[PDB]
Image (cartoon, rainbow, N blue to C red):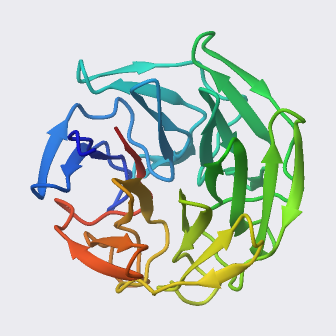
């Protein structure tokens, strides 16, 4: 039932880490600029819990220095204000995040040369982070999405090898299992869930930025390709609004895209949507 939810994009990178927060309304194609991030952020992830948007991890890279972030910050769309939250145990650039049972999971990402396999869990009611079981693989530039209270970490770079592998976190048991590997090596893909499938869109295969898109069907256990995007991209934002996937921005090996494409699983087609207000990669994105 269409009730006016918006796609939020926070931070990003375009000649330095950005502070933009903007919200897009797919039903009229308009963009609204909102309160800036307090500290510039790129390579962060976004998510929504209890009507609030959270900006997790990332980095501030500019001529004033390159520093990874352990920060968590919370934006209330109803007040248009950002508030700091307790930081993570470690900085995590190119993090993946998923929400289960009202808790935020921060997965992998990097701090300097360290590629984390560690995973930690944020409880909003306590403003507290708790380390959980680490992944089986170190993963930066990892994609994460949640389906039926299971969390999937897909692809990335482990510090030596760029990855086609993926693994599944069972939060009640606090354990990780490898799942079927993807058809393609992808770091910096957009990973989301739609219906019974975990999608991995675009990314970097170690040579080229990708326009291919493949999905893992959790029932059949296979990765299968679907229609490719029009524009190749890694470090894209991805989210699901009213039953369709949207990808936002990213880097195509030449430019930082303002392109937004929208995928309809019913027809297996991507359509072009109104451009971002400016090209950028490495954004955090969520819907509320």
Residue at 9% across, 55% down: 28
Q: Quadrant of the C terminus?
A: top left
The answer to whether residue 117 of the structure is visible from this angle is no
Eyeballing the image, is 65 above or below 160?
Answer: above
Residue with the most extreme top position: 126
Q: Position of residue 211 (x, y in %)?
A: 47, 85
Residue 141 appears in which quarter of the rendering?
bottom right
In this view, the residue in front, 116 or 245, is 245
Q: Is residue 8 left or right of residue 196?
A: left
Residue 197 appears in which quarter of the rendering?
bottom right
Q: Quadrant of the N terminus?
A: top left
In this view, the residue in front, 95 or 24, is 24
Q: Is residue 77 left or right of residue 254?
A: left
Residue at 16% across, 67% down: 274
The answer to whether residue 76 of the structure is visible from this angle is yes
In this view, the residue in front, 44 or 225, is 225
Q: Position of residue 225 (x, y in %)?
A: 59, 85
Residue with the most extreme bottom position: 207
Q: Is residue 32 left or right of residue 182?
A: left
Q: Position of residue 38 (x, y in %)?
A: 35, 29
Eyeballing the image, is 31 above or below 275?
Answer: above
Residue at 79% across, 54% down: 168
Q: Position of residue 23 (x, y in %)?
A: 23, 45
Residue at 26% across, 66% down: 279
What is the tally of numbered marks visible in this picture? 0
């Amino acid at each position: 039932p269409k009730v006016g939810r918006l796609i939020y994009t926070a931070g990003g990178y375009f000649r330095q880490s950005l502070s933009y927060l903007e919200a897009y309304n797919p039903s009229d194609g308009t963009w609204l600029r909102l309160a800036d991030l307090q500290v510039p952020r790129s390579g962060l992830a976004g998510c929504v819990v209890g009507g609030l948007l959270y900006a997790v991890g990332g980095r501030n890279n500019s001529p004033d220095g390159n520093t990874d972030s352990s920060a968590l910050d919370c934006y209330n769309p109803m007040t248009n204000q950002w508030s700091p939250c307790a930081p993570m145990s470690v900085p995590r650039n190119r993090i993946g995040v998923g929400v289960i049972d009202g808790h935020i999971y921060a997965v992998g990402g990097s701090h300097g040369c360290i590629h984390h396999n560690s995973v930690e869990r944020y409880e909003p009611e306590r403003d507290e982070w708790h380390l959980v079981a680490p992944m089986l693989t170190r993963r930066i530039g990892v994609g994460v999405a949640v389906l039926n209270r299971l969390l999937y970490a897909v692809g990335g770079f482990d510090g030596t090898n760029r990855l086609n592998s993926a693994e599944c976190y069972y939060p009640e048991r606090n354990e990780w299992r490898m799942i079927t590997a993807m058809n393609t090596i992808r770091s910096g893909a957009g990973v989301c869930v739609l219906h019974n499938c975990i999608y991995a869109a675009g990314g970097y295969d170690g040579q080229d930025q990708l326009n291919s898109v493949e999905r893992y069907d959790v029932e059949t256990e296979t990765w299968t390709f679907v229609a490719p995007m029009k524009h190749r991209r890694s470090a894209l934002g991805i989210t699901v609004h009213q039953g369709r996937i949207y990808v936002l921005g990213g880097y195509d090996g030449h430019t930082f895209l303002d392109s937004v494409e929208c995928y309809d699983p019913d027809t297996d087609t991507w359509s072009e949507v109104t451009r971002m207000t400016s090209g950028r990669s490495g954004v955090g994105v969520a819907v509320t």
